[PDB]
Each structure stands twice: as C-alpha cells, then as structure tokens.
Amino acid sequence: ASMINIISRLQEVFGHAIKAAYPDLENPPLLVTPSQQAKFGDYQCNSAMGISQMLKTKEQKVNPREIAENITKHLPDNECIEKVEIAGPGFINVHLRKDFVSEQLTSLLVNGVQLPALGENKKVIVDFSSPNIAKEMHVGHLRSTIIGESISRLFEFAGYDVLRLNHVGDWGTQFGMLIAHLQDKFPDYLTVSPPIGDLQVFYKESKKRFDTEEEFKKRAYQCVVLLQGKNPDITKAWKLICDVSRQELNKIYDALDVSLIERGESFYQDRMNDIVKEFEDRGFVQVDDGRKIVFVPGCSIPLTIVKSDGGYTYDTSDLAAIKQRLFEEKADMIIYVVDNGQSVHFQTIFAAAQMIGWYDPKVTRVFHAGFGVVLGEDKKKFKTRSGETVRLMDLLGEGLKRSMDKLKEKERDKVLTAEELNAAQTSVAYGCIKYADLSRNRLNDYIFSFDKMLDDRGNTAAYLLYAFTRIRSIARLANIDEEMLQKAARETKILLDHEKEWKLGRCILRFPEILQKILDDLFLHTLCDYIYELATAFTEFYDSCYCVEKDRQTGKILKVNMWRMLLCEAVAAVMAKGFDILGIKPVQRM
Ligand SMILES: NC(=[NH2+])NCCC[C@H](N)C(=O)O
Image 1 (cartoon, rainbow, N blue to C red):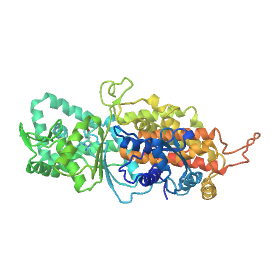
Image 2 (cartoon, helix red, strand yellow):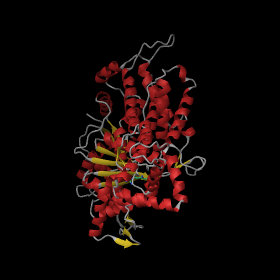
Image 3 (spheres, protein in one colour):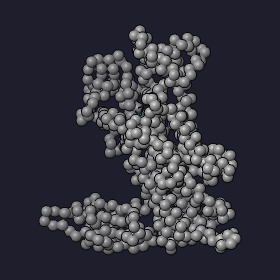
C-alpha cells in the first residue's frame, strides 16, 4: 500500500459535496490547498468563493458563505476529515482526523515510501543532456542532464514507463572538417585505430584548417555529403570520432550517476528521407533558394528541412524523431529538456507535427521543459577566462576539491576513509551541484556559485545532507537498530498530541501531493522547497520534543519514546526519496 494524495482525496470529497448541494453546476472550481497557519486547520477549500464568482452576474452576486454552508452540509462520510469550519467570506477550513494521519505515518514506515501506480501504463520519453559530438559539452548540457535525470526519476517513481533518450548532436556539418582532418593526420585510420587525443584540440586543429584553406573547406563539405551518402570509409571515420567522444561523455555520466540510451540525430537518417517526402506529398513544402522549407501557419519562422545541397538539418531530424516517438515508441508523453533559446524551434516543430496530423495535443502530451542560461557571479555567460567553454569534468573536479576542503575541519579524523575520502566528499559535491540548479525555477537564469552552493546553512545540499545525517543519528545513538525500528513500526501507535509532532506529521504526508503537482508543471524546485520545509519542520519538533531522556549525570539514556523515534524514521524515509528523485545521494555519517 502507498501514500495517499490528500489534496486529491479532499478534492474528491468536496467534489461529491458540491455536486450534492448544487447538482446543476458544471465544472465547479475545487481549489484545495494546505494551510500555512495551524490556526486555520490543515487544508483549505476555496470552491465556494470560486462558485459565487462563476454565477456572478450584473445584478446579482451570491454570498460565498451561504454556498460554503450548503457545501459543508453535504459532505459525505469520509475517513480523513475531523471537522470543517467556514471562515471569513466563505473559506472552508479543513481539520484532518488524528487517526488518519497517525495511521498513514505508520503505513509509510511499514510498506516504505511509495506512490500508487498508474491504473494503466504510460510511456514517457525524456530527451535530455544531448551534447554535440566533437564540441565541448557545456553547462547548458549539464542543466539539461541534471534536470532531465530528476524528471525521469520522478515519472519512474510515479510508475510510468520511462525511456531516457540522449539526442546527441552526431550528424552535423560539424563532421566535414573533422573527418577530412582525421584522414590527413591518420592515413591508416581504416586499420590502425587513430590516437585522437583530446577531441577539442583535434577540433581546433581542423577548424584552423577549415578557416584558412579554401580548398580544404571544399573537401570538408564533400565529406559531409559522403557521410549522408553512407560511404563506408567516411562512415568509419565518423564512428572513430564518435567513439572518442563517447568515452569522455561516459566519464561525466558516471560521475553524475545518469543513465541514458544514446540515440543521436544519425539514428534517424533513413526516416528523414520519408519525412521530407511526406511534407512534400501533403503539400506543405515550398522551394526557396534551392531549400525545401515549411511554413507553419501561426509560426514566426519556417522549418528548413532540406538545404540547397540536399543535406538534412536539425529541423529534419527533430521532425523524424518526434514522428517515430509518436508511432514506433507509441509515447503517451514526450518531454524535451532543452535550453529556452530553442523555444521557438520546438514550438514550430510541435506545430508542424500537429499540422500534418501526427498527434493531438489533447491526447498526447508534448512538452518543452526549458531552462535559462548559466551565469557566473558577474551575471554574464558562464565561461572560462577566457573566454571559452568550461570542461564539465573540471567543474566537477573543482566540486570534489572544495567538498573535501570543507570536510577537513575536521572530519578526516572521525570517519572511515570510505565514509569520508569518498562518501561524504562526492555526496556533497555532486549533491550541491545538482541541488543548486534544481532548487531554483528552471526557467530563470542560474548563477553558478561554488560558495553559495557549498554553504552549510540555509537551502543547500550541504545543509540538507547534514540534517539528514542528524536525523539518522538519533536512532543510531540510542542503539535502536533497523530490526527494532521495523518491529516498533508494526506495533507502535504513533502519537501526535504535540503541536510540533502534528505540524511534522502532516508535512510528511504532503510528499505525494507535492510530486503530483510536479508531474504537471515539471517544476522540480518545489520538491526542493518541500525537502527544506520538511527539515525545518523536523528541527522545530526536535527542539520541543525529547526522543530520548538520558537524565543528567551521567547522561546514559534510560528512556526511549519509540513513537518520536519513528517520526524521525518517517522524516528520513521521505527525505531519502526526495533526494533520490533529485539524483542526490545521502550519506549516513558525514
Ligand atoms: N530533440 C532535441 N532537439 N533535443 C536536444 C538537442 C540539443 C542539441 N544537441 C544542442 O546542443 O543544442
């Protein structure tokens, strides 16, 4: 059995009530939200304010308070509602039954923290990371990677069948000069696998040629046509160059703990020929300067689906890719995690796909989840002085360094070398790199700051991961092992008489409702906001309620309130999932 979405349950209850009080009213508002101040209950329903605002006319405006009255008068018998009260104009304040909350806290402790599955399976495709081969993967790709991983995890946790696609840029004209140069530098590449060093030095080598030698440029353009032509030798060089890129990428994905099925633009090369003919045959194609282009009614720009030279484009592959995901993959949802600079691009592509009838946005969710740019502390584009793209591995390396530094006051002397000399160091470094991104609205520009993100106090992974170790330490330092806790879970009636154990209990039980909202807006920062809220709710609890009494001298225990122990476990279980959804790896000791 799994956690219950209280907002959905409450919406279902007031739903039946409103239908009973006002049977002829259609699509009444059902805004149910958690109360911030315990004064006014645990949840609030505003539907009576919204209902009067529906029936509002020129001459007559019904009092919300009377509506509230009819609504509450028709509340069905339910398991979660203690009592309700009508407040102010017509706010409906909701108090949860103590039994319900207590029992649900127990339920997550015994069956673990988990979501109710989809009634029917659903396939979600998440298109993220997607660096360009031969060019340096940059912080834009980092964001996509971090955000996409966490989205994927969220839908997995929610029971969706998730396909993680790395839509890599491996079909550009970027390859012409690279291949030509490979051929010149390693004339035996066809047999002797060439020792390409850093792909970027090699790119820079061939780009100087590309920019200075007119005749070389021509070869490069031909290599691109031969590559599209599936020429064996040219294709072999393309594989060898991609191989080299792949091993570098795998370093980053392993570090970041990310799993991705590679499926670059090159994957769709056959399907692109069809895509072009299908737009031609349906009459959507216009010839312009030798280019085959497509105007989508409503859009600011046309799609270029074939260049003058017969070469396919980024528009061509996105069109091939969205089509195969709709028909072959039979996706119920496709999520594109790409920088906001490409909004216009994806808006036109989706428009193009609807125009030719590949999907109905009411039946299939197709969603561009964009994100703002990465800035330094100067509010200009995050670069390396000067003024070039920063190696992600360097970025990560600098994280691991600063994390260890933090730890050496003075924790190199408490923890195992494993506990520290990796577990805490890597956990904090990567956690802070992820948390600093995801904890802010993805849409906004993001100031990448090692100092802000590694800070021990406030909304950081450093605070939260530490708060997590403390919460675990309580049962640890009272010798209540995992078998005792599991046992206690099955037997102890969790008690919620204190103000702070009630605040904390009802906060814990909000986890499912938080996640479900994120499935709709794909705003992961509210999950962060909730982890932080949860930590704060815990600290307030702990500072008002003893989990163990040690009785002064000589401070050696002699009392364990097993229900406040369990509360601690429920907090950490929920925090642990949350971290997991964000791709954050909590440690035990730190
Ligand atoms: N379906 C997609 N277009 N996914 C994103 C591709 C991102 C592209 N490789 C870039 O560097 O900008």
